[PDB]
Each structure stands twice: as structure tokens, then as C-alpha cells.
Amino acid sequence: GSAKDVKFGADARALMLQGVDLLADAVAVTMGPKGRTVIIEQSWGSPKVTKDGVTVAKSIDLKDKYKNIGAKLVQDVANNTNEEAGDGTTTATVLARSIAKEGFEKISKGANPVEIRRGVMLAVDAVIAELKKQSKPVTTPEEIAQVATISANGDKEIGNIISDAMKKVGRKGVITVKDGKTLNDELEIIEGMKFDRGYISPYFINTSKGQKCEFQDAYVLLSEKKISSIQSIVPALEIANAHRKPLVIIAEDVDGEALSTLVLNRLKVGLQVVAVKAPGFGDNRKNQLKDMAIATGGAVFGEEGLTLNLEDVQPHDLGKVGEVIVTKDDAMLLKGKGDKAQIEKRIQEIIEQLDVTTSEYEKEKLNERLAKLSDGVAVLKVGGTSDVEVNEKKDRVTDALNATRAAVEEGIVLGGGCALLRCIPALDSLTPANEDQKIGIEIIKRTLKIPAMTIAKNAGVEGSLIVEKIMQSSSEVGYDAMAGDFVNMVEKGIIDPTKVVRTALLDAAGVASLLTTAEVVVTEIPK
Amino acid sequence: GSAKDVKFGADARALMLQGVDLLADAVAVTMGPKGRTVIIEQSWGSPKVTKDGVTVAKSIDLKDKYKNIGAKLVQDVANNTNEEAGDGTTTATVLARSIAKEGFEKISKGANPVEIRRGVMLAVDAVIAELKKQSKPVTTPEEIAQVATISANGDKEIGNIISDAMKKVGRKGVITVKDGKTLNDELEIIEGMKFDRGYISPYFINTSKGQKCEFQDAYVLLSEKKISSIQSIVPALEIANAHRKPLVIIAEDVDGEALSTLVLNRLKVGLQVVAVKAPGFGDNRKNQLKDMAIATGGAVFGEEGLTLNLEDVQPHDLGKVGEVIVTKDDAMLLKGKGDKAQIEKRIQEIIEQLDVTTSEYEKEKLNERLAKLSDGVAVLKVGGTSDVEVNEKKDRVTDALNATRAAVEEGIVLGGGCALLRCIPALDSLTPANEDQKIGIEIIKRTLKIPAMTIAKNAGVEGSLIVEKIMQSSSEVGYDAMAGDFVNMVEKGIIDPTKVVRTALLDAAGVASLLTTAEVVVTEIPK
Amino acid sequence: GSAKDVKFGADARALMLQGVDLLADAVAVTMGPKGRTVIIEQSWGSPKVTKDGVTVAKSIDLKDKYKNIGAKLVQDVANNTNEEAGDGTTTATVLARSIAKEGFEKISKGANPVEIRRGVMLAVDAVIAELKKQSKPVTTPEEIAQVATISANGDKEIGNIISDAMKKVGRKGVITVKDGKTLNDELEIIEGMKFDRGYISPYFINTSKGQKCEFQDAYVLLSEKKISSIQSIVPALEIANAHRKPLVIIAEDVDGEALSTLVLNRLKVGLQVVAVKAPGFGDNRKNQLKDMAIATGGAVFGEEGLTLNLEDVQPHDLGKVGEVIVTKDDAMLLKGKGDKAQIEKRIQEIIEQLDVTTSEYEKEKLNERLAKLSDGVAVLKVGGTSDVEVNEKKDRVTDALNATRAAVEEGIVLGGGCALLRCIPALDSLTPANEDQKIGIEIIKRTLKIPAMTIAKNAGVEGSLIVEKIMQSSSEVGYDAMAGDFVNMVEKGIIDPTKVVRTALLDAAGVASLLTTAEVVVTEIPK
Ligand SMILES: Nc1ncnc2c1ncn2[C@@H]1O[C@H](COP(=O)(O)OP(=O)(O)OP(=O)(O)O)[C@@H](O)[C@H]1O
Ligand SMILES: Nc1ncnc2c1ncn2[C@@H]1O[C@H](COP(=O)(O)OP(=O)(O)OP(=O)(O)O)[C@@H](O)[C@H]1O
Ligand SMILES: Nc1ncnc2c1ncn2[C@@H]1O[C@H](COP(=O)(O)OP(=O)(O)OP(=O)(O)O)[C@@H](O)[C@H]1O
Ligand SMILES: [K+]
Ligand SMILES: [K+]
Ligand SMILES: [K+]
Ligand SMILES: [Mg+2]
Ligand SMILES: [Mg+2]
Ligand SMILES: [Mg+2]
């Protein structure tokens, strides 16, 4: 119902190309090892300094609506590349700008831009096939460190710390990046089953040196129902007193009467007991409770289906741990005495639960439960003297982790934009159906030189001469823009994930070739 | 979604440098002993006069958003220096402006500002290592008075009063600054356990000369629960009457029945009794009650875990004090007869509780409880004729206290900016990795002369000649800008905390070297 | 977060001096016996005509924020002088303007304004010491009348009425200024225990000539609790009827049953009784009832602590008065037959209560209770034909009362600004530490001539010649600007309180010397 403005043909295409050019010129200064940073003002406080392509892209909107349409389309390119791969958003931005510009230049009266888009997609399919042909899998942790170092803008310490984390918790393990209160980055490996619930009562502390409660070779009593009655807690204390062993009671809550009995026995006579709240807020809480019961070799009390009551507890019904530590904010369990076959059965049940999940929030919970069962988690705390530096380094650490995961799952190719440079003869071996498909193939062929040219241009040298020298060299030889020399890319460690490269190319081409099919642009009249 | 303005390169860098220069020029007039003050207009009332760098920094925002970005970044520098150290914010501001200016001057086509930032950080690490090498610990109260005098803009009385406070309550004791109703500053030492709760009933006054209640060698009855029944108070009164000794009932509250019994026994027959509310509003109330019971050698009645009732009071169960003073707004306990070993055990329990605490509010409560247990607290009341003078002097007193604590924990170096001046040959003994790292090292080397130059410039002399005369002199010789003479800085008392200097340098460098890496600035279009 | 404007140095200082000069020029026309008045527009109603310096100062705000900062600082000077002394705000304003102007003129590149402020404070301390040296105590009521006459702009009737009030109720008694419906001012002395509560029932009138209840030698029944039941009031009526004496019942309230019994006995059989609500609204009500019980020799029934009951009343328990007057809006008790020792004990208890309070509202209640127990209160009703004249005269009456109290508590010095003129040789005896302290001492030395110059300037003569003639004359000789001659100021009654002069000088100097230390002024952008 709102009044609209309508533009036709070359003027509208030039306006959207101006928007695409502005956004891509802002993004492209951050590309490569000699790329610079972008400062974006934030309304609520300190500005954000970033080297991330999708962060620069998503922070740009234009007053002109025709320019803003192209800006939003390249924003879609960068956001899709960030969601699919987690890296390569600047490459996707410059590839999309190149495809849009070369497609806008090729539109005439007799041209058919839809068939040009068809040829573009055929050429991109050929290039992706060649990229999959020339890729090799990751076999050594040195390649992991090299990938994480290249993806973190040459930071060797970030790559080394990611390699150490992947050595400790596994290449498919859980690694989480967070802030740090120190100047330097640190890696913390959390082993066993550690959850975010401390002790209910502060009188359970038997080690005042760290304000924590520690036991060795303790019984574990697991329950989903809240323990409140005297009769629900006396028999477990009777087993723990008869066998002279400590007892940790993990439950949803411990109410007043049961906690009064526990604190009275802890203080007056010296009973080794500690109460712990059950982590989770629903079905995840019961799933985690079952995981600790399986790991400790105990059964869960207050089951909704099995109906196990706390008034008849057996010594075999209690789990066992070699070590437990409970603090103010967290509790952890070490060396559970559970049966290994049941632990493995729960592990593959979690794995089969991971096969069918699309919410991308239950997937993280299942991965966390698998890590707590198998090998623990890794926490990367990013150091810095201020919040802006911490955020700037955290973006690079997240990029390096995403690229390391992509390289683990799909392999590596040559870095520096040389992987796309070696797929040009695959396009030279193509037979187009007509003239418009040939135009699209030539558009993709000219676009394939763009990332290496941008990386060389950001280093202060002429990118066309560098690209020609790379193409005239052997397949293993590329350009190192840090040292500024022509080297062996694999031996020098300049490598890229295959998934990142193909994702950036496909996501750029799909939106840019559709943008180049436009004849009429309809916008709203600015009020 | 809002429309944005995008600027590239030298114009955006010049605008950010204009904002940084404006804020730093406003801050830099307050530096040194000949620095002046800044008047900031307050909307709600009287303007604020200050000599504090972070106060001037946080009070400046610019209508130009490109200038405001640099202003916010140097605001972050000043605020981080204030949060980590509590002093040295003007030095951090001028160092950050110098690093930003010299890094903006050094950007060209072939320059790599990220490697320049790497060299800046390496040079700052070398300078911090040299500062820790040249630092010496504080060993005498004369050095404490000298540090507090230098940090309070040459006020000898503030330094003397801080030295007296640190002599009385300890160098790690609790000292609190507040306003004063008198012209002159005063120091009040609160010894023993004094809390903010007065008597419940005004009929408990036995000393009408000061409208207060005083007893000597009194029993103490401490209750975690509110005393409400008559039967909960008859046995304690019976013990106090049989032993003929005063009773101080520290409880959560006293209801109508127990209070009427207390006033009736006070007035009709002459029972020496007084009732006082338990200080605190939660877990801290029970913690303070436990510390009072441990110091007085008694037990807390109505315990949530131990379940001690007030109907079974014993003479050994009651605590003892040598003197208790009860005032309308406060009550205090002197010479508790508690066991020294249990008091020491509670003291190290509080100390170990202090080791694991990051909330920075429980830390203050634990420090206050430790001070009430060990050595009391100190209160500095700042004098003046108006609120603006009191606030202006209170800023300097807070600065002097922060610098004194920093000098206690980390030692002292030469004042007047000479400590950074003596770390230049440590940078001269550095081998850069490449040209950009060499550029960053030279940036830090030129920046290291800035604080002494600013201090000398604020004194009306040429700072470059003064700086050159300092470097041509011995390592113990610096410039006194008050006398305007070249002196021995340790013998004249012109010294600085090492922590303040390294904090200011690191916080300036970390943000300014990241600001100098910028190529594109994105701001919001002003509505 | 709001956008700010920042000004540096001489331009900012000139704008602040423009604001200070505007507000001080408006204030200074009201100074001395030949000062004029200022009309301030009020939004709600009629404009206000005043000769008060703090009233003129607080009513001025400027659109220019740089000028408004200086205006607010001189407002702070005037308000601090008004709150500390109650008089001398015009003198403080002109002294502050002089110190600000002389400090602004003396700022150069080599000047240190903080040391100038230190020298200003040292000189002001020397002048205050000389003022305390030359002060004389007040010994005669003629000096009281002279002080109150000078402070009331030469009004001899106001001074005489204040001297009469201080003669009747004491020099430290309670005197309250209020409006008058008559053309002329009047002084009313309220003796005994008069409070703002009338009788509960209009049937208690036994003297309809003034619509009042009139009894001689009456029993008094004082109750802290409400009297509602029949049996709560029958025994007291039985003692009153048996001894054949009138009964005034001062209680919190009287409910329907007891009131109906009282009115039935008053109308039918002719019982001399009257019921009166207890004055106060809380703890002050109980305190006032206790003072009435002590003064009348009775006891308070329904006390919360002692728990006295109205069902067992003894003839000695009731208080006695020689005369009680009950009026529709107020009730008074005369010739209480209480024990003199207990009255004195209550008086010293109230006196000791006054030394441990700072709320300034409980102090008024304590002083009112002490006046009702010892000497009564005085009410000055200010006459006039309109509200504007009544307010204008009430400001001068309040000024004269404040100056009379200050002269009682601290003594008197020479008026007309001659007391500050005689302190100049004390500054001539000073030895400055450096050049900036010498500058500050010279600033204060030139400032000391300002009040006499302003008083002579308002009289229409050249103030510099007058000040030179005063300084060349004897120490007892000053300038009567009212008569325009040179006289003995003590013999002519032209005297000032020492407290007012030293308060005005200290309050002016403390703010103005801090204002002259500024280099940067930060204001908000006017929206
Ligand atoms: N020393 C180097 N020499 C040559 N090329 C390099 C070097 N280091 C990195 N590269 C290449 O530079 C590219 C990395 O650029 P950059 O990480 O800034 O952008 P991106 O991966 O496209 O996107 P994002 O901004 O999301 O990280 C990769 O192609 C990588 O192979
Ligand atoms: N008499 C003096 N001679 C030379 N240098 C001095 C003298 N007194 C102090 N200084 C130096 O001046 C500096 C103190 O400046 P100032 O306290 O105004 O600023 P700051 O500490 O950087 O910041 P903040 O505004 O937060 O206090 C220190 O480097 C100190 O060593
Ligand atoms: N006849 C007189 N001859 C000379 N000086 C006089 C005479 N009468 C009063 N003065 C002086 O004039 C001053 C009184 O001025 P004024 O009361 O207007 O101002 P103030 O006390 O500074 O302030 P405020 O406006 O609060 O009253 C005093 O210094 C007093 O000694
Ligand atoms: K990038
Ligand atoms: K400063
Ligand atoms: K006046
Ligand atoms: Mg990357
Ligand atoms: Mg300081
Ligand atoms: Mg006056």
C-alpha cells in the first residue's frame, strides 16, 4: 500500500553496484595477513574494532535504498558463508562483488542473464569438483596448528593452543572460547563430569584451604525428586555409616528437614556427606542425571517410569567415585566406578541421538554430554588489557577454531587464493552450451583470480603481476604476502580448508548471479 | 538497520586523532605538581572541579561521531587505568595519545599496522620488564608518607594522615574516606567490633552524659533467631542476675513481650541489660554474629544447623566483654574474652575465603570482618568549607590511598616520569624482527619521554630540554617541577608506584596500537 | 553520553568571570544602610522584593553555561554563608567576586594557581586569627539591640523588640518569626506549657466570655494510651469529685464512652472536667507528656515500659496545676506543682540530648521542650499592609535574629567592613613561602578593602577615599555611611558579629580560590 519508486535497467544496476562496491570496499581492506581493521561505532558504548568480513558487512546500511539492496545482498552472502563455514566471509564478499560487476558489465539487449547465471553455476560446479579433486585430508597435528595459525592472522600462539586443545580433548571434542582476566591466553582442560552447581549448605566444607569439599572413594546417591523427608534420607546415611564411606547426594533439591539432618550429622558427629543440586532445567537435567548414574555405576532414584523410591536403598544401588570436589559454584566427579560396557552403550546412544537433530541447541547439549562422558571439554580464555582487544582477538580465535573443524572434516587445499587459481584450467576444459553460458564461464574464470589479487593488493604490491607469476609457476608454488616471496605453500604452512573455499565461492555465486538477472528495481519512497 | 556513514583511511584517521587530541589536551593540563583543574558542568546542581584524569576523560563526549570514537577509546584507556590501578590516568591518557599520533603518522602503503602493533607490544613488554628490574620494595613508613604526599599533589598533611592510618590499622587494613563537617581533615580509628545498630529501647541508657549505655565486664547473649518468647529470655536474665553481671543481647530483633520484660526488669528492680539488633541483612549478618561469638567466647543461639535453643543457656555458653558501649546509632564491644586460638582460626578462615572471591562486594565484607577481628578500621574525614572543595580534596585522598596500596603491594620507582625515561636503553638493546616491528619499537621509544615532558611543560618550562638533561644525568637524578631543580628523586621523596606506571603504559599501548590498525570507520548517520 | 563543549584558558575564565560579575553586581546593590532592593518575578503570583544577598543570588540563572558555572559557584558561596551564619551573604558574594577577579588577573604561563590558592588560604587563616584576636564578647542588652538594629537595616524597633525578646526568654531561648495581620509588629511571650491541642468536647466551656475552659488549682491526669472504657475514667473522676478539684485529662484521644461519661457529668451534676488531646505525632508526643508529668508532679499512664494502668489511680499520682486555660485551638498549663529537682533533672537530660544530635529537626523539638520547661517562647509577628512588605521585613527580622544569636555565641567586632580593614597589618606581617603564595596573600590583602568600599559606593561617595581615611585613622574610628561621617563605631553602635564576618570571608575564599585554579571548562551542548 505504500508508495513506491521504480527504476529500470542500467541506472538501477549502477546504483546497486555502487552499494555492492561500497560494502565490498569496506570489507576488502581486512583480507590477508596484511589486512587492516575496521572500527564500527556502537550506540551503547565503546566502538568495536574487527577484522571479520561478516561483522563489517552486517554493520553497513545505506540511506539510498537502491544501494542498500545490493548492500543487503552482499550481507546475505557474508552471513550465509559465516553460518555454513564460520570463515571465509571476506573472500565470499570480494568474489560476490566481482561476479556482480562482471555480470552487470555483460548485460546487453541480446544478452540472456538467466542463461548467464546457468553458465555461472555450471562453472562453479566444475571449480568445486576440481577443489574436491585437489584436496588432501589432515593427518598431523602440525597441519592443525598451521590451519589455526593461518586462520588467526598469523598468530602462532593461537594455533599452538588450538592444536593442544585438539590433542587433549580430541579433534571432534568440545572447545569453548571465553574472555580472560589475564593478559595472556590460557587453555583449561576440564576432565570428568563437572557441572555448574555447588553445595547446598556451606557447612559441608571439610577443606577450608580452598573453601571446598573433597572426598576420596565416595558413594553417590542420585535422584530426580527433591529430598525432603527424614525417611527419604536416613537409609542412605545408614549405608554410608555402615560402610564408613563419604556420600555425595546429587538431587533436584534438598529441602529443610533433610538438609537439617545432613548438617546436624555433618557438624555434631562428623558424617562425611555433601548435598549437590542437579544441573539442568528439564529433560536435560534427567539426561545428565542418567549420565552420572551410568558413569558412577548407580541407579537414578525418583524415576518417572521405573518408580524407584529412596526408602529402600541398597549398597549396589549407590554409585562410586574415586574423587569428588564440590566448591561454591561448581562440583566435579572423578574416576567413576561404572561399568565400561554401559558407558559405551550410553555413548553410542548419544551419538545416535546426534544423528537426528536439527534444532542446533539440542546438538550442543548432546555434544556436551558426550564430552563429559568421553574426554572432557577445553576452555580457551582470551587475554587482553581491554574489552575491545579481547573481542578483536576472540573473533580471530573463533575463526581459527571454525577453520580447524572444517579442515578436520573436509581436508585442506593451498592458501592465499591459489586453490581457486589452480581450478582455472578446469574451466578451460569446459564446452559451453551457448553464448550466454560462455559469458558466465568467463565471468567465473575472471573471478577466480580475485582473492589472490586482493591479498597481494593489501600487501602493497601489484596483484595482477603476482597472480600471473603464480599461474606461471608450479602447482605447489604460491605467494607468501607476509614475507613477500614465492614459496611452497604446504611446506610453509599457508593452507586453507576446502570447505571454507567452496562455501565462499558457492555462496558468492548463487546470490551474485541472481542479482545480475535484474531488469527492474522497486523500492519504497523515503518518508 | 540504521543508515551508516563510511570513511576510509587518512580522513577517518585524522578525525579520530582530532577527537583523541581534544580529550587528551583537556586531560593533560592536570598533570604533575603544577597542573591545573577542570570544571565540569553538572546538570542537577553545582559544577565539579577536579584534577583527576579519568574524571575529565569520562565527562567528554563529542557531537562528531568520528571524533567521538577516538574520545571513547582514550576514555577506555583512562577507565581501565583507574580500575586496575586507581591512579595514573593522566599519564595513561597522554601515553595513549602519543602512541596513537605516532602510529597514525607511520601508516603508508607498504606499512603493516598489525606488525607495528606487535612491535609496540614487544617494546612495552621489554619496558615493563625493565621497570620490574629497577623497582625496589617499600620498607619504611617515611616512604609510605612520601608516596601518599606525591600522589595527593604535594599535600604533606594527607600523606602524614595516610601514614598514621597505615601505622595504626596496618598497611593492608581497611581505610575509608568520607566527607567532613569541619574545615580540617581528621583520622578516626575504630577499634574492636563496632556495628551500625543502636539499642532497641531508649530506656536502656545508664549514662545520660552522652545519652549512651555503658557496661564493664558484661555477658553477651548472641541469637541468630529473633527472641520472641518470654521463656527464651528468662534463663539468660536468671544467669545474669545470679552472677550479678550486665547482659548485652545481640539478636535479630526483640518482640514486644521480651522487650517489655527487659524494660520492666530495668526500671522496676534495676537489671543491667541492653538489647541490640544483629547487624547485616542476610548471610553477612550470621557471619558477623559468628565472628562476634568467636571474639567474645560465646555461641550463637538459634543456629540453622546446630539448633541451639535459648531455653538451655549455660554460664559458659554466654560470651564475655570487658567493655560495651551502646549509642543511638551504633554499638561496640571492647576486650572480648574469647579464646585466641579460635579467633586465629576464624581469621585464617576469612583469609582463605578472601583467596577465592571475584564479586568485589563479598571481598569488601570479608575485609571488613577481618579488620573487625584483627585491628579495627580507619576513617579519613576530608575537611572543607564547601562540597566542591571536599570532593576535589577527596579525589586526591582516594588517589593517594590507591597509590599507597599499590606501592605496598608492588614497590616503588622514580617519580616525575623518570622511571619510563630510564627504560629507553632497554629498548635500544632490542633486535626487531622486521621493519614494522622496528617502527613500533621506535613509537614506544619516542612515547617514553612524554610524561616527563608533559610534567615539565605544565610547569612553564621547555620539556624537551628538561628531558635531555635528565637522560644526560645519573640514574638517580630527576627533575623536581615544584622547586624547578635537578635533584635526587629518592632523597627528595619524588617516587611513584611501579604498578601505576606499568598499568598506565600497558593500558595506553593496548588500545592505542589497536586504534592505529584501522583503515575503515563506520558511524551512524546523525538524525 | 551527551555531547559536550570544551573551552580552554582565558576565554573560559572570562566567561565564568562574566557570570560571577553579573550575579555579584545584582547582589551588591543591596549592601549597607544605603543599599537598595531587588524585585524577583515569581511564576505563581506576586513578585518578591528583597534586600537579601542569598535570595538574589539563588534567583539568578544564566542561559550561557560558562557564565552559569560561575553564577552557581557564587550561589554556593552565598548559600554556605547563609546556612552557617544566617547573615553576611552580600559580603561573602562581593568578597568571592573580588577573589575570583584578582585570581583570574594573576594567571600566567609561569603561575601556579594551586599554590596561589594555598597562599590565599594561609592569608585567610591569618585574617581569621586576627579577627578572633580583636573580637569582644557581648555583655549588655544594649549591644544586643545595637547588633539587631544594624542587622535589620537600621530599624531601631526591630532591634528593640529582639532585645526585649532576649530579655524575656533568654539569649539562648526560642524566638519564632511569623506574619502579622496588624500594621505594626508585636512580641508575644508564651509562658508555661502551651500546646496546639484544643479540647475534645465543646461542652467543657465554663467561661463563655472567651469561649474557653478556665480552672484554678486543677488535677491533671496524663495518659499515654487512649482512654476509651468507662472503668478507665471512673476512678479518676472519683478522686476529682471526692477532693472537689477540677480535672484536666491529657490523653492521646478520648473515645465515645468516656467522652459521653465526661459530658454527662459536666452537664448534669456539674463536674469540673476537660479532656485534651496529647500534642505530638510519635515519640515526641510521649516525650512532651513526660515533661508535662514532671512539671505537674504526675505520672504518665499507659506507658509502654512501666505499664501503668488507669484503673488504679492514687491522689498523689495525679499532677497539679495552679491554672489551666483550654481554648478551641490550644491549651496551656500554668503554675505546675512538680518537684523542682526532677524538673532540673529533666532539663539537664534534654540539654545532654541536644549535644548528641545533628538532624536539625529533633534539635528544634528539643529546644522547644527545653523552652516550655524553663522560660517559654517568644513570637515576633511582623506587621505590614501587604504580603510583599511583610516578607521583605521578615527577611530583615530573620537576619537580625541570626546576627544576634551569632553575636551572643561568638562576640562582636567593628561594623561597616572596618573589622576586615584592621586585619591588613596581620597580612603585612606574613612571610610567603614562594611567589605564588605571595600572589595569593596580595589577593586577600586587596580583597579585604572590598566590603567597606561597596558600603561607601552604595552611599554615593568614593569608596577608595573613604577606605584610605579609615585606614589612616585610629583603630576605633570608622565610616558611618548612614550619617556620612567618621565616628567611633562602638559608641555609635555600628558593630558586626565576628562569626558572620569570618564565615563570609572563609566561604568566599574557599570557593573563589578553587575557581581560580581552572584551565579547562566542560559544558553540555545547549539543545
Ligand atoms: N602469509 C600469507 N601469505 C599468503 N596468503 C595468506 C597468508 N596468510 C593468510 N593468507 C590467506 O589469506 C586469506 C585469509 O584472509 P582473511 O582471514 O582475512 O579472510 P577470510 O578468510 O576470507 O574471511 P574472514 O574475515 O571471515 O576471516 C586466506 O585465503 C589465506 O590462505
Ligand atoms: N614535585 C614533583 N616533581 C616532579 N614530578 C612530580 C612531582 N610531584 C609529582 N610528580 C609526578 O607527577 C605525576 C603525577 O601527576 P598526576 O597525579 O596529576 O597524574 P596521574 O597520576 O597520571 O593521574 P591521575 O589524574 O589519575 O592522578 C607522577 O608521575 C609524579 O611522579
Ligand atoms: N550606618 C552604617 N554605617 C556603616 N556601615 C554600616 C552601617 N549599617 C550597617 N553597616 C554595615 O553594612 C553591612 C550590612 O550590609 P547588609 O546587611 O546589606 O549585607 P550582609 O550582611 O553582607 O548580607 P545579607 O544580605 O545577608 O544581610 C555590615 O558590614 C554592617 O556593619
Ligand atoms: K578479513
Ligand atoms: K591529573
Ligand atoms: K544585603
Ligand atoms: Mg579468516
Ligand atoms: Mg595522581
Ligand atoms: Mg545583613
Image (spheres, coloured by chain):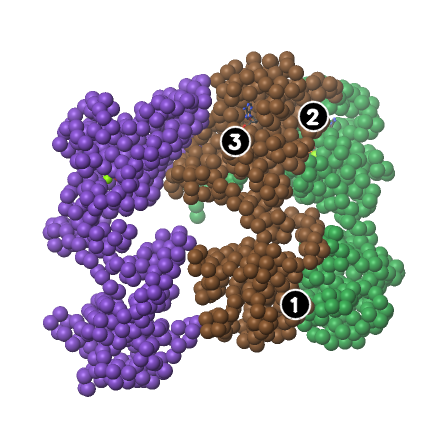
Chain colours: A green, B brown, C purple
- Residue at 56% from the left image edge and 72% from the top image edge: B241
**First reached walking from the N terminus: tag 2 or tag 3:** 2
Amino acid residing under circle 2: Gln
Disc number for residue C253:
none
Q: Is residue B114 left or right of residue B203?
A: right
In the rendered view, tell whether residue A241 sits above or below residue B438: below
Whether the residues at callouts 2 and 3 have beta carbons within 8 Å, the answer is no
Q: Dot 1 lies on which element?
A: loop
Q: How many residues crowd mark 2 within 10 Å: few (<14), some (14–19), many (20+)? A: some
Please give the residue where the numbered disc 1 appears in the rendered image. Answer: B317
Where residue C222 sits, quadrant-wise, is bottom left
In the rendered view, tell whether residue C326 sits above or below residue B434: below
Whether the residues at callouts 1 and 3 have beta carbons within 8 Å, the answer is no
**First reached walking from the N terminus: tag 1 or tag 3:** 3
Asked whether mark 3 and ligand 2 are closer than 8 Å, the reply comes as: no
- Residue at 62% from the left image edge and 42% from the top image edge: B170
Disc 1/disc 2 C-alpha distance (Å): 57 Å
Task: Report the chain holding disc 1.
Answer: B
Task: Report the chain holding disc 3.
Answer: B
Disc 2/disc 3 C-alpha distance (Å): 26 Å
Q: Dot 2 lies on which element?
A: helix
Amino acid residing under circle 1: Asp
Q: Is residue C500 left or right of residue A527?
A: left
